[PDB]
Amino acid sequence: AKNMNVRPLLNYFEPLFTWLKDQNKNSFVGWSTDWSPYADQSIKVRIS
Image (cartoon, rainbow, N blue to C red; front, side, top):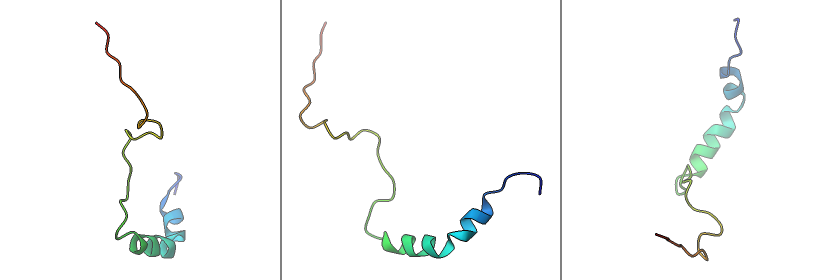
């Protein structure tokens, strides 16, 4: 080919991908960008 292709890299990690997809039946694949490790002791302030 003439371009950098990502398919071979994914072919390299096929067994690991299978085993991971199996080991995460009960986890939550993904993340939410709102939780932060200090948002529980924070105090909100509004000013007008």
